[PDB]
Amino acid sequence: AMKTLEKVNYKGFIWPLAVGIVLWLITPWRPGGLSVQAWEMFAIFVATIVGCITKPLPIGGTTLLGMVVTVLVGLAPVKDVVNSKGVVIQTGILSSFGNSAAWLIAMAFIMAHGISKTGLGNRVAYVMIEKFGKRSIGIGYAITGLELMMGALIPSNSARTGGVTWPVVESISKSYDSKPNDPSRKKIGAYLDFMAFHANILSTALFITGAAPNLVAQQMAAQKGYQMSWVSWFWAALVPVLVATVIIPLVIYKMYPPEVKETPNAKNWADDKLKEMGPISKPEKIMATVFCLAILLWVLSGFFKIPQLDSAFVAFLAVTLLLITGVLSMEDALHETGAWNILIWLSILIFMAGKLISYGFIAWFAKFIQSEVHGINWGLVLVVLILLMFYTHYFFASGTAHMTALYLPFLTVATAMGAPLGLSAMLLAFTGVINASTTHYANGPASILATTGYVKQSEWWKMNFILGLIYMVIFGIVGTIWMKIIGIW
Amino acid sequence: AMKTLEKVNYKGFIWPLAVGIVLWLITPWRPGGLSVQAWEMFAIFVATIVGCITKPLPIGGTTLLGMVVTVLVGLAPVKDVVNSKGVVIQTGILSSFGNSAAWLIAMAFIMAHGISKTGLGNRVAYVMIEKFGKRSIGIGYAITGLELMMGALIPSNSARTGGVTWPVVESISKSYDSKPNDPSRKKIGAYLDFMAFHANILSTALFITGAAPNLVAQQMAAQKGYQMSWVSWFWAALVPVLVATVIIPLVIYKMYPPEVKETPNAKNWADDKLKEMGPISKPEKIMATVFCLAILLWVLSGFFKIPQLDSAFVAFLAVTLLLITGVLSMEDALHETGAWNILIWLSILIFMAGKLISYGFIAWFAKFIQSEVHGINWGLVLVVLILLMFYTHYFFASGTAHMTALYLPFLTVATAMGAPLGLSAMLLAFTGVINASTTHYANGPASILATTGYVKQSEWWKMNFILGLIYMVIFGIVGTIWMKIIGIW
Ligand SMILES: CCCCCCCCCC
Ligand SMILES: CCCCCCCCCC
Ligand SMILES: CCCCCCCCCC
Ligand SMILES: CCCCCCCCCC
Ligand SMILES: CCCCCCCCCC
Ligand SMILES: CCCCCCCCCC
Ligand SMILES: CCCCCCCCCC
Ligand SMILES: CCCCCCCCCC
Ligand SMILES: CCCCCCCC
Ligand SMILES: CCCCCCCC
Ligand SMILES: CCCCCCCC
Ligand SMILES: CCCCCCCC
Ligand SMILES: CCCCCCCC
Ligand SMILES: CCCCCCCC
Ligand SMILES: CCCCCC
Ligand SMILES: CCCCCC
Ligand SMILES: CCCCCC
Ligand SMILES: CCCCCC
Ligand SMILES: CCCCCC
Ligand SMILES: CCCCCC
Ligand SMILES: CCCCCC
């Protein structure tokens, strides 16, 4: 018996629509050397992002709407178009949900549901509160150190986030009664969410085995005659990453403070709650075993490249084990909405960014940069290249496509303007790492920790912009001094 | 606070496991001319189906488990493997959820949720009960006639089912208080579910624009020198389809009777309920408009082949309209479990069948048939070919791959054993149509109407086997007499 329609934010359609429309009417006056379909896809993508901002039809709905409009105005098919030789010359909106990152994140949400159902997350939370609970910044630094230690083993940031630290964040927040999409999110949950994201950034920056784009940078620098190694990257990123570990958390605590700042009796409270939770149970032990097994497969995935260890099949396998074991039914995994919502909208955004890359937008931007800056001292050239490689990730959603597309061209321009090779390589790599401090779709950890409701998106974008300025200053200046020190030039 | 694990049917793992194991140990003694990977994939597929039967880890769980085992023993990657020329020589478990049929069915489940929420389904149900409510077989024949009329326009059976008649079935069942997965399913819901499936079969058989496999048969017969036309197919399938319309419902009513057989006062009851529902509302009017628009796009999709009318993008578009209009939020579409469950398990089954087709199983079966039957009167040859083209669809899940793979070879053998061309073509086409009376994954309508809980799977398979024998008798004998009558030979 439904009487009245649901409440929809129609005002939020103004800025997206308008933006799109204007760019569309601008199409004939496009920057030149560019294709009509490219500019149209750019306009639709920008309007979709402005919608994700103004939040009409929450991100799933507006992403579906942007995909629909993409298919209507003739920028994308529904089924992949083949060249009669098997090659897929055009992808479709259906060939977008077969993405590894989105399915990994969904299965990780499901594993997190299992951790929350068993009672393991809350036990871990009270343990961490007994250890470093008081002075919540202590909790933030502990999660930062945990992520840093895990960076050396787990080569997938999306896993390090949705499998280990996002559950810990959720549990610690639910022990403080910090629920999402509620004015009670500001207690401790939002601070911890943000700090988890930025600790994931730091860990990705410290170890070359912290993410894929770093490996892509390695392959490229080897293409141009510079061999990045686990020890060199580490010895170069140690100092700047320590400076960041010391600063970034402090400015987050000063800018986005944890409303609940002090817990003078965390020890007794955690002990009381644990003892009230009774001894550890069988489903909790099984979930712990499955979690340790998944972590083991993830850390082995760095030495053995094998389909059985794709870092997503591992999540499928853990979920399957939870199903055949009992701690997780199938209905428990079916109405875990976050999984399907993120599947939908992340897949759609990645598809639209891929269409931006294929239609010849990024390549034109790269040629423009290559033909614009001609005579300058290589210092300003490197500054400009870092700034561009930073603020171009607003038009990407993978982090690997960004590098494959813009790392070799910008590095080439730098080395051609007199800059040294190792410095430019490592700087553009650190920049491709800290790019994540731009958006809510920049990577897996952001697409996870921005949509949990603990942190709004306006605040997310603003604070990430500021912290990106800070990251660029830190890495550029400090790491340049550091690389001049240790024989990199 | 979870204490005890969930209840899992461990006994149901015996038959699948055993089966698999045995076939695996049989591998060295495989039929010959076959590949090891092919026989292993066959074993895993068969065990997965036996699991879907015995129901450990409901179909979603056992399909996930079969996919996991597929990836573990080295039969499928997780990411598509390319040949360095762009061609995809091996598909992955992730490149399986980008399927048009599964996403169409999911979006149709969502549209059905909208129809049930608005109050439109119940109004339609009481209308149909006022018209042909008494003598529930009247309801079955009305739904049959509706599906038959829609066959001439909507060229997608999955849509005709999940968009029009599955909602009507659900509403009429919920007006009789027939809920699924309940001993109250036998009242009227199961009979109507079965009858809807078989009416979809009949409509697919009557009009060549009733499904894709019929178009595939058309293309093939044109390849071999026989031009199927909308008027010829219809004039040949009229008589047998009338015989089926008269018989099949009767044997279903005699074999699977609708426990509630008589409703002597349907008129007054429907009028009372309608008047108690008040005049038609605004959300109902909007859902009706969206439904009519989707039906219009679906019927236009037969004359204009355009990505904007893919018969799945239309469901995406209807859902998007319901979102931007208000009658359907995003949370309403996120916890619609059936959509995601069918996505999962149908995609996985289609992927495994595609692996059966690529590894060289179906092609070997076809060569075996081509090299086995050599000297026979073409009548027994056609009998054997119809039987094989019928009972090979247990190893397929699309209905189009089946035809593309086995229609031209069997038709070739028939025409080479003396049989006439038009007769063999039309008979194998009708057989590719009635193949759907085999399984729960044979097509979209079956994968929909078998998993709704109104009809079990054991009963489904048994009754579909019997009705397939009956369909083969009817079509073969009657249609052969009919084609001999009208100048087809
Ligand atoms: C004609 C294209 C106008 C721009 C499309 C706006 C898309 C809205 C997505 C929320
Ligand atoms: C050109 C981008 C304009 C985006 C404006 C977003 C305003 C959001 C107000 C809450
Ligand atoms: C748990 C996945 C381990 C699978 C082992 C695969 C070994 C392949 C050797 C060829
Ligand atoms: C010496 C080249 C590196 C300088 C990078 C400075 C970036 C400034 C960010 C605001
Ligand atoms: C060694 C492979 C045996 C096949 C097992 C298949 C398991 C599927 C269970 C649903
Ligand atoms: C290939 C043999 C399949 C056996 C299936 C038996 C099902 C038993 C259900 C009670
Ligand atoms: C509802 C969308 C109908 C299709 C728009 C017109 C496309 C014409 C492309 C030539
Ligand atoms: C003349 C032969 C026509 C084919 C008859 C098919 C009968 C199938 C019997 C099950
Ligand atoms: C001529 C400069 C225009 C650049 C617009 C494209 C980058 C957003
Ligand atoms: C006012 C609702 C508009 C919906 C977006 C349409 C995009 C062309
Ligand atoms: C380049 C986009 C900027 C993000 C918002 C900045 C608000 C100060
Ligand atoms: C307790 C026996 C279940 C084993 C399941 C393994 C399926 C490959
Ligand atoms: C060699 C005899 C036939 C075996 C058939 C195996 C099942 C397709
Ligand atoms: C060749 C497969 C036949 C299976 C028939 C199943 C009847 C319940
Ligand atoms: C030009 C619009 C800025 C937002 C980028 C996604
Ligand atoms: C959140 C993962 C905790 C596992 C403890 C063994
Ligand atoms: C357990 C993974 C081992 C991989 C050996 C190739
Ligand atoms: C293959 C997983 C075995 C676990 C059964 C309890
Ligand atoms: C009853 C199991 C059927 C096996 C063929 C798929
Ligand atoms: C079930 C669809 C009903 C639409 C009536 C106009
Ligand atoms: C509410 C539907 C509007 C679509 C055309 C702008």
Image (tube, coloured by chain):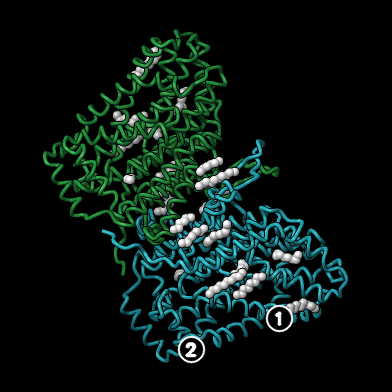
Chain colours: A green, B cyan
Look at label 1 and name its amino acid: Val
Up the image or down, A39 lies above or below B1; here it is above
Looking at the figure, which quarter contains the N terminus of chain A? bottom left
Q: Quadrant of residue B284?
A: bottom left
Instruction: Identify the residue under disc 1.
Output: B473
Q: Is residue A115 visible?
A: yes
Q: Residues within 10 Å of mark 1 (few under 14, many from 20)?
A: few
Up the image or down, B397 lies above or below A425; here it is below
Q: Is mark 2 within 8 Å of ligand 20?
A: no
Residue ID at (48%, 14%): A373
Look at label 2 and name its amino acid: Arg
Residue ID at (35%, 42%): A164
Residue, far left: A264
Host chain of mark 2: B
Towards the viewer: B345 or A133: A133
Q: Do marks 2 and 1 share a chain?
A: yes
Q: Quadrant of residue A456?
A: top left
Instruction: Identify the residue under disc 2.
Output: B135
**Residue B303, image x and y in percent?**
63, 59
Residue ID at (17%, 34%): A135
Secondary element under disc 2, as helix, strand or loop, is: loop
Q: Is mark 1 within 8 Å of ligand 8?
A: yes
Up the image or down, B328 lies above or below A75; here it is below
**Residue A375, image x and y in percent?**
48, 8
Towards the viewer: B94 or A148: A148
